[PDB]
Amino acid sequence: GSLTSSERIDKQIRYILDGISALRKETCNKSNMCENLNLPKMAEKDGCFQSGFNEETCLVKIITGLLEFEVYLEYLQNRFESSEEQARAVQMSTKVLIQFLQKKAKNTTPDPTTNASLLTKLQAQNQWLQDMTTHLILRSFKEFLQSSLRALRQM
Amino acid sequence: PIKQIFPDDAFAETIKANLKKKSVTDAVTQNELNSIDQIIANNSDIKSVQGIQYLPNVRYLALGGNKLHDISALKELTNLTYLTLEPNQLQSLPNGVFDKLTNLKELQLWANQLQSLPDGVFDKLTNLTYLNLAFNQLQSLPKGVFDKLTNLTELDLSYNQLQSLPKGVFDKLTQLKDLRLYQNQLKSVPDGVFDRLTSLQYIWLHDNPWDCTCPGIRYLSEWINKHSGVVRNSAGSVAPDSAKCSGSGKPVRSIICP
């Protein structure tokens, strides 16, 4: 169904959000960082807000951003000790998510090679930078999901 | 007025918005009530749906949220076809909630503080083509739990704490095409468990800590090798090797017994 599928996506996102919240807790319990990277962000032009809403361009953006987050999600593996099953679950449930959004759609991936070296570049940095990268992934992937969640609720 | 018919505060706002009314004190016609066939009220603050029984033609229902416990009034919506039910805090399904809802095609039941499914609970739902019991925290399934569900084509049991499966659990599901068991605690499955699933197109087994000690792993290991196409990863792609042994991290299907 349409209501079934839409509930099922709503639910999958909420589960990822809970997870992110766990990693958040664990990380700024070390960094206190909760108040360059070019991380995927929603802008009014993407069609996802209530002023300027557009199903088709919103949905393309959701799926493109999520696909861009993936390498940042890979970065996240083994930077967590008490909340690692979740670190893994977040990575894996994003994939399931992207798969649900694709069945929903009609009509652009990232290159693995940039991603292989962007990833060694982030992993190469000092411990403060490493944690600063983490807090920003978590923060921006979260805002991204929330924005995706509100819009899907209106599609 | 609406607030009289639907005594719950949030449920009255749902209906008000559903009908394009200006306040919860507006009167409603027999026409307005007769013609609601879809109610969308997941992640709401509803505690009770009392009043819903005055809405005989609801076919599509999404219902759920932190505060919900009182769903007794669902029982006589004999037209309900698509139901998504998410009572976050609920601990016990009312005796035979689903018994009179025999036109149900699609049932999503996400009730994570429930922990045990009462036996018989799905026995009247013979028209179900799709059952989703993800996100509960199920340690086990009761015997015979899916037996009357002859028509299921999609069954999703992922994100639970299943440690084992009942012998024969899927034996009556010959139309099943899609079966999800990922993100549980399966150490193993019983010999034969998939043998009757001759329509299976997609199965997901990854993110279980499988026990690969021989001879126990035999059946599963050989099963995965002999349906290398059905076995899928989180991105929906073919990945026989996604099923992995705990500790070691080897592919289950890389284990060969004497």
Image (cartoon, coloured by chain):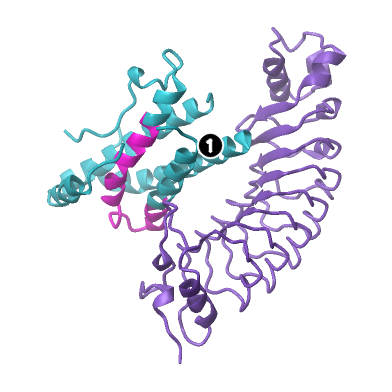
Chain colours: A cyan, B purple
Q: Nearer the viewer, residue A62 or A72?
A: A62
Q: Main secondary structure of the magenta part?
A: helix
Residue A38 image-quadrant placement: top left
Q: x and y percent of residue B141 in the render?
A: 68, 64
Q: Position of residue B19 (x, y in %)?
A: 72, 15
Highlighted magenta segment, given as a residue range: A61-89
Q: Is residue A32 visible?
A: no
Residue B18 point in image, percent of width and height: 69, 18
Where does the image place residue B80, in percent across and percent down from the top left?
78, 36
User: In screen coordinates, is B9 left or right of B161?
Assistant: right
Q: Is residue B161 visible?
A: yes
Q: Is residue B197 magenta?
A: no
Instruction: Tell me how many marks there are.
Output: 1
Q: Mark 1 highlights which residue?
A: A10
Residue at left offset 48%, top offset 66%? B208
Would residue A114 be found to the left or right of residue A83 on screen? left
Position of A51 relative to B241 (above/below): above
Instruction: Inspect the image, locate mark 1, and give the three-letter code of the amino acid beneath it.
Output: Asp
- Tell me which chain the residue with mark 1 is part of: A
Rendered image quadrant of residue B123: bottom right
A40 shown above or below B14: below
Report the residue at 60% width, 32% height from top. B43
Q: Is residue A70 magenta?
A: yes
**Residue at left 67%, top 66%?**
B170
Of the pair B211 and B104, the residue shown nearer to us: B104
Residue appearing at x 87%, y 15% in the figure: B30
Viewed as shown, does residue B55 lie left or right of A111?
right
Secondary structure at numbered mark 1: helix
Eyeballing the image, is B55 above or below A112? above
Crowd around label 1: few <14 · some 14–19 · many ≥20 (10 Å): some
